[PDB]
Image: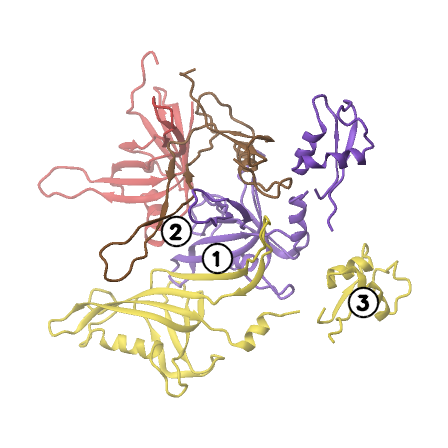
Chain colours: A red, B purple, C yellow, D brown
């Protein structure tokens, strides 16, 4: 913009999971990008370049981090998939906020489910917070702005 | 309805004209194949004598066609639009086999098949199938399987002669344009210039060495016995 | 009992109707296979004459089916629920071979097999087997082995004709609905419209060109000699 | 016209002297193949008697030749010079098959190429 916005003020909301204020707060969000797979072809007589063709649109997994929370609803949802193969996909909204705490821009993440859950190593000789990490697979996203 | 994702269908038929449907004989897939493939073969006769540098190549036959594709069955619960079933993929595979594989006691054979998806339309017979079962519930109910298929091509014999409109055996007519001569036109119709006096007698022409440029002529076929 | 992990079983039988069990002839595995695979083949006759663009495809036969899977035997002591045995896997493999491979002097052949796991139920014969021995105790007692298996399919001949309910040879009845004509119904039952005067005589019809819409007709078969 | 990128063509013919064209029987590709390949075979007679150290080699025949190549059809919209069509590649493949494959009832055979 004339002065572009910073990246440290944002909100993560879930649809299909009971809401709690402690499940909307995160330390970091990553994975909001996309790419197109292509193929190459050489045409006889054309020596200046090879041709390139698109094939598929590709998205990476969405990664969320925060300090450990013991009564999380999101984690209970993750456990049902992890332990029993019960899968029930959800939708999600990522919001980048302005100074009035209203959205500048949002991302609509469609049909997501859990593929990973972990907690970082313990160390008796270091002063650190216990950090939890969750990774989700999804089909695509759209933006609103 | 451009925006609709069309799904591949297979219907079973009772007769060789494809007009009498088998009752409850239609299969619709839930996931489309990635690709499909065709095969075409033409056979020639290539006998030659010793001492020569090249062979006279004679047409012999056009061989039947072939279509191949792969399918995936899955009822795990991550694909949008579908529900998880109590028995998984058991009824999906049993209905698929009843359409394409099973023997029909009314006709003493398996079924005629029509395969349609978008621009594709193919009639024929199943030749080969392999089904491999991949995931299971703890009590042994399958929830994922993969199938490979090969289809042959069927043409009814009355339709083959209508598509091969086989024509010195039939009758012909032309109109005379300026620049035409009678022995050159006879060569292009019969393969030989020597029949020009029989074409002129069948049309009542006396001055055949000069043709007038609006005349319609007939070209009779050659006699057989 | 949804939560129970079911294990694959194989039982041996004495008769071709699968009702008389071999005594001590049941095998139960300790580890399930990962997957299994089926195979289906249909054969056609494809002779054609030279000069033509397509062949008339005739049904010939349906070939027998095939099932394949792999097994693992292990008595090392890291799998929960089982104990380490003094002789390892010696009695597990010897009981497995007695069921599926060994010649039975009462019937002068190997055994009939029924294979059941969850949704699967298959009857037939063993064709092929390979067993490879992997780990050993210091005195030469084996504790791990891998087996690959191929099973054919068996149908008794009295049951084949009941499954192929083969039907111009049998009798038939229909009820007349509005819109029916006698020569169109004769074509769909016999394959030819020309038998309409024999159908009308066998039913006592005089005004057959107008049928009343509640009548039940008979359709006799054609005579054979 | 050195600077012109020439495109490969296939024409169908009616007679064995290649002078009478099939009407609407010409195909022009939109993308050239990468390469092509030829094959040549000569056959000899190599009978010899036992006890000998070499054979008398006699010429027998020259066998027919062979050409092979590959094609690509694409109407996605990233190749400069062409337009996207409502029906894609349906009419491109149907015209290609009519030239090189289909049986001709006037001559009772497929076409000369």
The residue indicated by pointer 2 is A86
The residues tagged by marks 3 and 2 sit, at their Cα atoms, a distance apart of 57 Å
The residues tagged by marks 1 and 3 sit, at their Cα atoms, a distance apart of 42 Å
Camera-nearest label, 2 or 1:
1
Image x and y of residue C18, in percent: 47, 79
Residue at 88 percent across and 62 percent down: it is C208
Image x and y of residue A79, in percent: 33, 49
Is residue B214 in sight in this rendering?
A: yes
Camera-nearest label, 3 or 2:
3
* Circle 2 residues within 10 Å: few <14, some 14–19, many ≥20: some
Q: Is residue C79 left or right of residue B7?
A: left
Compare residues A17 and C170 and report the one nearer the observer: C170
Image x and y of residue A99, in percent: 34, 19
Residue at 56 percent across and 40 percent down: it is B118
Checking the image for residue B178, the label placed there is none
Checking the image for residue B128, the label placed there is 1
Residue at 27 percent across and 54 percent down: it is D55
Is label 1 on the same chain as label 3? no
Compare residues B48 and C45 and report the one nearer the observer: B48
Eyeballing the image, is A89 above or below A140?
A: below
Q: Is residue C7 left or right of residue B148?
A: left
Secondary structure, mark 3, is: strand
């Amino acid at each position: 913009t004339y002065y572009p916005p910073s990246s440290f003020h944002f909100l993560v909301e879930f649809t299909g999971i009971d809401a709690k204020n402690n499940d909307h707060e995160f330390q970091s969000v990553s994975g909001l990008s996309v790419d197109i797979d292509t193929e190459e072809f050489a045409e006889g007589g054309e020596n200046r370049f090879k041709h390139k063709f698109p094939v598929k649109t590709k998205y990476p997994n969405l990664v969320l981090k925060r300090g450990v929370l013991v009564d999380s609803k999101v984690i209970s949802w993750c456990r049902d998939a992890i332990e029993d193969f019960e899968f029930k996909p959800i939708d999600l909204t990522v919001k980048l906020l302005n100074e009035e705490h209203q959205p500048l821009m949002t991302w609509n993440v469609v049909h997501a489910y859990p593929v990973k859950w972990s907690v970082e190593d313990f160390n008796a000789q270091e002063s650190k917070m216990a950090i939890e990490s969750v990774e989700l697979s999804y089909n695509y996203f759209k933006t609103i702005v | 309805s451009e925006g609709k994702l069309e799904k591949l269908r297979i219907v079973a038929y009772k007769d060789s004209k494809f007009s009498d449907e088998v009752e409850n004989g239609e299969f619709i897939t839930l996931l489309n194949p990635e690709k499909y493939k065709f095969q075409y073969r033409v056979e020639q006769n290539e006998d030659q004598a010793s001492g020569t540098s090249s062979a006279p190549i004679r047409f012999n036959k056009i061989l039947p066609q072939t279509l191949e594709f792969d399918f995936l069955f899955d009822r795990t619960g991550v694909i949008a639009g579908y529900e998880v079933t109590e028995d998984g993929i058991i009824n999906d595979i049993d209905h698929f086999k009843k359409v394409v594989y099973d023997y029909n006691g009314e006709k003493h054979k398996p079924n005629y098949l029509m395969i349609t998806w978008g621009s594709l339309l193919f009639k024929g017979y199943l030749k080969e199938m392999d089904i491999e079962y991949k995931l299971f519930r703890p009590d042994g109910t399958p929830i994922r399987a993969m199938a490979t298929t090969k289809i042959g091509e069927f043409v009814e014999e009355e339709l083959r002669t209508a598509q091969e409109n086989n024509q010195p055996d039939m009758s012909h007519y032309r109109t005379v344009k300026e620049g035409d001569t009678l022995p050159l036109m006879t060569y292009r119709i019969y393969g030989d210039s020597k029949y020009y006096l029989e074409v002129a007698k069948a049309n009542g022409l006396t001055n055949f060495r000069r043709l007038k440029t609006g005349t319609e002529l007939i070209f009779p076929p050659l006699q057989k016995q």
